[PDB]
Image (cartoon, coloured by chain):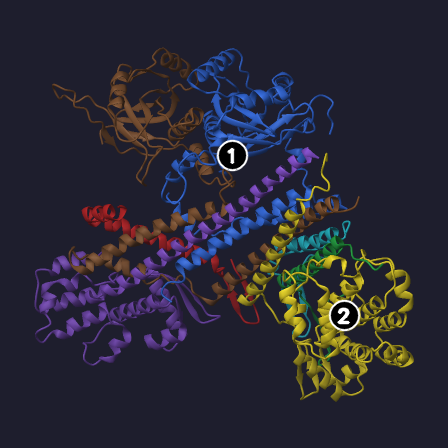
Chain colours: A yellow, B blue, C red, D green, E purple, F brown, G cyan
């Protein structure tokens, strides 16, 4: 709480990244406290205080890395992926272990959230594609095995390279990917079938059991990732994929919220652009 | 009519004539540098009304006349239109002898009263013959443009306008000699064989503050057509076409980027503003009518 | 004008589209208001003249 | 994606699938808006870090 | 209309002839609103005596509906087919006055008829006489009414309608006020933006600075 | 009454353009004077056009130029054949002795001149254009002259109707300093105001009828009942679904259309940042 | 051969005609705009920096 109190009264504007953010994120990560630091991560952080040159680049890389771990502890994979992407794209022509770890966790989170590794923006530093990638090789082949869509082979590959994952403290993320492969396969099944037997689903997803397949489908229905119903008279599962019809005030409210966010973004961009034009750096004769 | 301004408004400076600025812009001659210079023609309400009335009053014959105004920047302003005592057949008009005496005398008399504008163009009516430049209009417009440079050819169709309920006014300017530079072919068809010789212009209309104030009380029974306006239903095809052209403009701007984005943004803003205005009118109607006795 | 659904044995002649009916009913309401005002003016010209004069000021 | 159909393995029937144009359009427009907002919020931080000239020395 | 001749020819009559004329009026096709007739002094004084049943029947025709008629079937004198048809048509008009979408079950209950064909025929023949305009629908079993005539009103209910009209006026006023507020705010926004533009004006002052250096 | 006069919606536009142009030229508002033309059919007078006139000032008196009028009369006959001088117009408020002096002077040209008065600086919703007729009364002694008020009509040609509708529906004449939202909402405000005035008159009439101070009409009251039993127009569920669908569609059209404007502002900002901040 | 606009329901032995596909082409147009905007967004986020 001391650093949380210090941040509001020492830094100027709520959109300003400071070095003490990294320290507070480290304290929250090491103390297994994730709730107090939430309001300090939900707000997008723009502009960095100079700190009279005392703000080293490392303090930046830590803030978007340790905080990323926080978003992997609260099951918020989108913001974790965004934080890891921001950490990776830092322009720096020197190898750092923080960048390597951020790249590995970015690969893992992209494999968990989506069925493939999200393509990094092309404006990132070229050192990532020259030194970072060759050193982080087990994660790339793990991604390849995940993309080939063979749940049986993923377990064997995890067993083969267990020592690398345990050395890098990743026992708890790759297993989530292995578990989510089954959900991805089930969703792809819903992309084709309309009414499927539980035994047939167990055989296709290699879940080895109709009861286990029923339990997985029930869990996914509870989570909301899938739209399905279970008829136990014949042990069948049906898919009713008609969730929204876009005829209710709720979607109007959603569009209103998107409009408000876009308008605020545009106003902030215009204010920054008008602030930029004061400097006489260029535009002399052109 | 209250809670606003009643003095000289922001739509009255268009009616003001500055002699010094016109003399400077006539001496500058910026048209000769870039030949695709003029692209907009702003016509007063009075000029358009007089043109339409004179074209329709001629019946099946063709009529012709002049139009006064000025030029500013990239736009040509046409303020007044006065007819001519021409005797034309169903196809061709001549304006042999009495037309030129009428031109000179009318310009002098108008200058006597206070009309400070000079002649800015000529117009001629096609009685049901579309809106395009014929092989004789092209020649005469080239003749006028060679020496009296600020000029524009306005073509009006009275019969088609009265039959379809929409005015058909086209502003055109001719390229000089030797200036070469499921989609419909009407782009080439609706022009004559000289389609590559002349180019059209964007026609817009304007009116003064007193004009709008007096036209507001023109008639008190269009309120029914405003309450039961049924917007977003009579111009859905217009909005779909605008969206298509906007997508094409966005593609062109994206290709260029890899200043064109400004006009694409303007078109998108215009279409969105029209849609939002329609929705606002519908919401107002719903609040007015269906929210009573619930 | 209309179509036939054979299994249900139903001939559909025509159906409205809601919003155009809304506009038509609004127009009919406005016409009724205008007709009632005209009849009111016709039956008591002096009273309606006085009422309009009072309302204008 | 070669054939748009759904298999019903209860009576073994291949049903045809009709895509709802309005719903798909709305969903993809919302997805595009979300992606654009994320890209903007990333680019603003990129510009801010470029102004400070942050790099590992 | 037609009631003018009836009231003119019944102005100077009284007694059993008055009851006969009342029955003829109730049997006369094309007459559906008996408003001016009830204002006659003879009909008003007909209340006292042994012929009050005719006045009650006239009041029921003017204001009441078919269920009210069947409530006192024995009290009122017997009626022919034309009177019952007119009463049913007036009941349909009264039902359509409240709601513009009348279910078939409600019409069957109030009009006391069994077959759906009979109800459809009655509605069609009521549409023919132009008292109401609308379309039937068998898919959803409902009748949609676009326009209906204004039935007779009592003297003491006028304030009622007045109230409703007042409400409408109020609503209009509210809407107008809101519109004004909106436009004012819009204008303010515009002016605020123009202020920002004038701030860009200050920029050329910095240009003067580069004149010094 | 008197002579039925038919006014076209082209004279008024001529007067308004005249007034606007001379006010802009002189900086300050002035008084404009011209001459009307039209046709005389039996007991009917029709005014269909007008041309400007030249007037001089001698101290306080205003004198209409005659030679210029004669030249204009000879000139205008070439284009318009069945057109004759009918009256003369001016812009002003209440009648003035200067107007009566000008009318008496103009009377030397035509037997029965009209007098069209336009109000460019009106301060009410009353009709700003008024047609006055000056018939020489037989009052002896001093010439007590009061121009009789005329209830003019709005006789209009078909092409005139088309042009008038086109200019009335015009909206691009502004869209400058004044927001287009204001122009869009003004029409709705005026329409709602007129509907509210009509329904207020109906409410006043029914209140008077229920008060008992006016004769009781059994037909108008039932017509009012029929009108008042239908305010909730088409409150079905299908209409609500259609309305929500339209609102959602317009919301999507606004989202796609704000995104592009934000992207354009993005492009401008990045272009400015890549020159004034980029190190070459 | 595109001479009959309809489909065949084999289970119920039915033929369903094509009294559908109303003027929803507007949506299609919007779709185009969508993808265009997406590309342009990238062109602003990776224009130069």
Residue A59 located left or right of residue B150? right
Residue F271 located left or right of residue A169? left
Residue occupying the point 72% across, 36% down: A284
Check the picture and name the quadrant holding the C terminus of chain F. Answer: top right
Residue ID for mark 1: B205
Is residue F270 shown above or below A102? above
Numbered-mark total: 2
Residue occupying the point 45% across, 53% down: E182
Secondary structure beneath disc 2?
Answer: loop
Q: Are marks 1 and 2 on the same chain?
A: no
User: How many residues crowd around disc 2 within 10 Å: few (fewer than 14), some, or many (20 or more)?
Assistant: some
B244 and D11: which is toward the camera:
B244
Residue F272 marker: none
Can residue D2 be seen by looking at this rendering?
A: no
Check the picture and name the quadrant holding the N terminus of chain F. Answer: top left
Is residue A271 shown above or below F248? above
Is label 1 or label 2 in front? 2
The answer to which quarter of the image holds residue D9 is bottom right
The chain to which mark 2 is attached is A
Can residue F224 be seen by looking at this rendering?
A: yes
Residue occupying the point 50% across, 55% down: B279
Residue F271 rendering spot, x and y as whole percentages: 72, 46
Residue occupying the point 40% across, 27% down: F28
Residue F274 rendering spot, x and y as whole percentages: 74, 46
The answer to which quarter of the image holds residue B288 is bottom left
Secondary structure beneath disc 1?
Answer: strand
Residue G10 rendering spot, x and y as whole percentages: 69, 72
The chain to which mark 1 is attached is B
Residue ID for mark 2: A114
Residue A117 located left or right of residue F161? right
Residue E31 rendering spot, x and y as whole percentages: 24, 61
G25 and E124: which is toward the camera:
G25
């Amino acid at each position: 709480g001391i650093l949380k109190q210090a941040i509001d009264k020492m830094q100027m504007n709520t959109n300003q990244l400071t070095s003490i953010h990294a320290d507070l994120c480290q304290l929250c990560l090491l103390a297994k406290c994730f709730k107090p630091a939430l309001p300090y991560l939900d707000v997008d952080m723009m502009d960095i205080c100079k700190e009279n040159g005392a703000y080293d680049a490392k303090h930046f890389l830590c803030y978007y890395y340790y905080g990323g771990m926080i978003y992997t502890g609260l099951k918020n994979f989108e913001r974790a992926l965004y934080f890891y992407e921001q950490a990776i794209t830092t322009p720096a022509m020197a190898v750092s272990h923080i960048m390597l770890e951020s790249y590995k966790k970015y690969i893992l989170v992209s494999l968990i959230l989506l069925g493939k590794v999200q393509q990094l923006p092309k404006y990132t530093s070229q050192i990532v594609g020259r030194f970072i990638k060759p050193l982080s090789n087990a994660y790339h082949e793990l991604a390849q095995v995940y993309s080939t869509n063979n749940p049986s082979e993923l377990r064997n590959l995890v067993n083969k390279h267990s020592e690398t994952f345990t050395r890098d403290n990743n026992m708890g993320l790759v297993k989530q990917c292995l578990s989510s492969l089954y959900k991805k396969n089930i969703q792809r099944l819903t992309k084709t079938f309309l009414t499927l037997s539980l035994q047939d689903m167990a055989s296709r997803v290699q879940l080895s059991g109709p009861q286990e397949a029923e339990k997985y489908v029930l869990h996914m229905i509870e989570d909301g990732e899938i739209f399905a119903s279970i008829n136990q008279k014949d042990g069948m599962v049906s898919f009713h994929d008609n969730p929204e019809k876009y005829n209710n005030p709720a979607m109007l409210h959603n569009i209103d919220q998107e409009m408000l966010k876009c308008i605020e973004l545009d106003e902030r961009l215009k204010a920054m652009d008008q602030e930029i034009t004061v400097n006489p750096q260029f535009v002399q004769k052109s | 009519l209250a809670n606003n301004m009643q003095e000289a408004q922001s739509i009255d400076e268009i009616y003001k004539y500055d002699k010094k600025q016109q003399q400077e812009i006539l001496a500058a001659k910026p048209w000769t540098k870039d030949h695709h210079y003029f692209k907009y023609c702003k016509i007063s309400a009075l000029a358009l009304l007089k043109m339409v009335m004179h074209a329709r009053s001629g019946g099946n014959l063709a009529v012709m006349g002049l139009m006064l105004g000025k030029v500013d920047g990239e736009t040509m302003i046409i303020m007044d239109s006065f007819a001519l005592p021409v005797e034309g057949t169903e196809t061709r008009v001549n304006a042999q002898a009495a037309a030129y005496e009428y031109m000179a005398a009318y310009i002098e008399n108008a200058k006597q009263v206070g009309r400070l504008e000079n002649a800015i163009g000529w117009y001629h009516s096609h009685p049901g013959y579309g809106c395009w430049l014929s092989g004789i209009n092209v020649s005469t417009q080239m003749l006028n443009q060679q020496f009296q440079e600020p000029f524009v050819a306005v073509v009006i169709d009275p019969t088609r306008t009265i039959s379809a309920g929409k005015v058909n006014l086209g502003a055109f300017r001719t390229y000089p000699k030797g200036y070469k530079p499921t989609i419909p072919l009407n782009k080439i068809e609706d022009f004559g064989v000289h389609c590559k010789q002349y180019y059209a212009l964007e026609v817009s209309y304007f009116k003064s503050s007193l004009d709008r104030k007096l036209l507001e009380l023109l008639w008190n029974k269009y309120w029914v057509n405003t309450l039961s306006s049924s917007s977003l239903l009579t111009n859905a095809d217009y909005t779909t076409g605008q969206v298509f052209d906007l997508s094409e403009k966005l593609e062109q701007s994206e290709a260029q980027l890899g200043d064109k984005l400004a006009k694409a943004t303007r078109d998108s803003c215009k279409t969105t503003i029209e849609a939002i205005h329609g929705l606002m009118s519908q919401v107002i109607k719903d609040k007015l009518f269906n929210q009573i006795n619930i | 004008n209309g179509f036939i659904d054979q299994i249900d044995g139903i001939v559909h002649f025509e159906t409205r589209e809601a919003l155009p009916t809304w506009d038509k009913q609004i127009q009919s309401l406005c016409f009724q208001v205008n007709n009632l005002l005209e009849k009111i003016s016709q039956t008591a010209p002096e009273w309606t003249a006085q009422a309009m004069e009072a309302q204008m000021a | 994606g070669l054939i748009s159909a759904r298999v019903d393995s209860h009576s073994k029937i291949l049903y045809a699938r009709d895509v709802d144009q309005r719903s798909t359009t709305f969903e993809k427009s919302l997805l595009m808006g979300k992606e654009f907002q994320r890209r903007a919020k990333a680019m603003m931080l990129r510009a801010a870090v470029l102004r400070n000239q942050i790099h590992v020395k | 209309n037609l009631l003018e001749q009836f009231i003119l020819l019944a102005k100077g009559t009284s007694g059993s002839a008055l009851t006969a004329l009342i029955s003829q009026v109730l049997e006369a096709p094309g007459v559906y609103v008996f408003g001016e007739l009830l204002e006659l002094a003879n009909v008003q004084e007909l209340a006292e005596g042994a012929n009050a049943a005719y006045l009650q029947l006239l009041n029921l025709f003017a204001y009441g509906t078919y269920p009210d008629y069947i409530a006192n079937k024995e009290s009122l004198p017997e009626l022919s087919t034309a009177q019952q048809n007119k009463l049913k048509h007036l009941t349909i008009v009264s039902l359509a006055s409240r709601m513009k979408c009348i279910p078939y079950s409600v019409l069957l209950k109030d009009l006391e008829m069994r077959n759906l064909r009979e109800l459809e025929d009655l509605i069609i023949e009521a549409v023919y006489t132009d008292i109401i305009q609308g379309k039937l629908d068998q898919r959803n079993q409902l009748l949609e009414v676009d326009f209906c005539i204004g039935r007779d009103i009592r003297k003491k209910d006028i304030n009622n309608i007045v109230k409703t009209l007042h409400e409408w006026c109020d609503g209009c006023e509210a809407v107008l006020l809101g519109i004004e507020q909106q436009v004012l705010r819009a204008n303010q926004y515009k002016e605020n933006h123009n202020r920002t533009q004038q701030q860009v004006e200050a920029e050329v002052t910095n240009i003067k600075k580069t004149l010094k250096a | 009454g008197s002579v039925s006069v038919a006014l076209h919606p082209l004279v008024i536009l001529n007067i308004s353009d005249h007034w606007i142009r001379m006010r802009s030229q002189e900086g300050r508002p002035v008084q404009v004077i011209g001459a009307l033309i039209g046709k005389q059919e039996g007991r009917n007078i029709e005014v269909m056009n007008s041309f400007e006139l030249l007037s001089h000032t001698v101290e306080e008196k205003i004198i209409i130029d005659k030679e210029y009028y004669y030249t204009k009369e000879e000139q205008f006959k070439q284009v318009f054949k069945e057109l004759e001088f009918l009256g003369w117009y001016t812009t002003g408020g209440p009648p003035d002795p200067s107007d009566i002096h000008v009318h008496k002077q103009v009377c030397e040209i035509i037997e029965s001149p009209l007098f069209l008065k336009l109000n460019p600086m009106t301060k009410h919703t009353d009709l700003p254009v008024s047609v006055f007729e000056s018939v020489i009364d037989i009052i002896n002694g001093e010439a007590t002259m009061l121009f009789a008020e005329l209830t003019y009509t709005l006789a209009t040609e078909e092409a005139e109707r088309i042009g008038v509708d086109h200019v009335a529906r015009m909206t691009a004449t502004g869209s400058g300093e004044n927001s287009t939202v204001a122009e869009h909402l003004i029409a709705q405000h005026s329409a709602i105001k007129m509907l509210h005035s009509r329904v207020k008159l109906i409410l006043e009439y029914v209140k008077a009828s229920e008060a008992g101070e006016v004769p009781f009409n059994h037909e108008i009251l039932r017509e009012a009942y029929a009108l008042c039993h239908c305010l909730p127009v088409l409150s079905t569920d299908k209409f609500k679904t259609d309305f929500y669908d339209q609102c959602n569609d317009v919301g999507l059209m606004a989202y796609l259309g704000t995104i592009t404007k934000t992207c354009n502002t993005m492009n401008q900002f990045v272009n400015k940042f890549n020159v004034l901040y980029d190190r070459q | 051969d595109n001479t009959i606009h309809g489909r065949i329901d084999q289970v119920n032995q039915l033929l369903e005609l094509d009294h559908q596909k109303r003027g929803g082409a507007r949506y299609t147009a919007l779709d185009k705009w969508t993808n265009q905007l997406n590309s342009l967004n990238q062109a602003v986020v990776s224009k130069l920096a």
